[PDB]
Image (cartoon, rainbow, N blue to C red):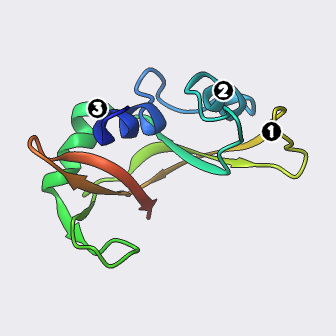
Amino acid sequence: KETAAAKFERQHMDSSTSAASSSNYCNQMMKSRNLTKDRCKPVNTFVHESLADVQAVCSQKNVACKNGQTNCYQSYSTMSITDCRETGSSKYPNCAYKTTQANKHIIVACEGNPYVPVHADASV
């Protein structure tokens, strides 16, 4: 089994690129990060910042999570991110995604020791 921290890293970290400069970015990333196995993950965000920068959010602005829990944090600064969302033409195993690059504040849920991100709770 994958640890919560490791899963967050695989699903949401992409520090190798400063931004998604192609419409095929999501199709490639969703496939390579294994998010289209057995089924197409409907929505998923990738953050283009260092892992250290994202982990640091766990000690930044404490905010409520969508579910009401209180272990969520909002990044003080905006970050380069790419949102991936299935398109109408998407049909597993032939998943299709729209790539939307943007700069926004990320919101993550943190847990453990070390206290690190374990869930992506949107972005502002």
Q: Position of residue 118 (x, y in %)?
A: 31, 48
Quarter assignment of residue 82: top right
User: What SS does tag 2 mark?
Assistant: helix
On the image, numbered disc 2 is attached to which residue? 31
State the quadrant of the N terminus: top left
State the quadrant of the C terminus: bottom left
User: What SS does tag 1 mark?
Assistant: loop
Q: Which residue lies furthest to the left in this view?
A: 113
Q: Which residue lies furthest to the bottom in this view?
A: 68
Q: Which of 101 and 107 is in front in this view?
A: 107
Closer to the eye: label 3 or 1 = 1
The residue depicted at 57 percent of the width and 47 percent of the height is 44
- Amino acid type of the residue tagged 3 in the rendering: Leu
User: What SS does tag 3 mark?
Assistant: helix
On the image, numbered disc 3 is attached to which residue? 51
- Amino acid type of the residue tagged 1 in the rendering: Ala
Numbered circles on residues, count: 3
The residue depicted at 55 percent of the width and 27 percent of the height is 33
Q: Where is residue 63 in the image (x, y as percent from the top left)?
A: 25, 72
| Mark 1 vs 2: CB contact within 8 A | no
Marks 3 and 1, Cα distance to the nearest angstrom? 27 Å
On the image, numbered disc 1 is attached to which residue? 96
Q: Where is residue 31 in the image (x, y as percent from the top left)?
A: 66, 26
Position of 123 relative to 14 (above/below): below
The residue depicted at 45 percent of the width and 29 percent of the height is 14
Would you say 44 lies left or right of 107 here?
Answer: right
Q: Earlier in the sequence, mark 3 or mark 1?
A: 3
| Mark 2 vs 3: CB contact within 8 A | no
Numbered tag placed on residue 58 in the rendering: none
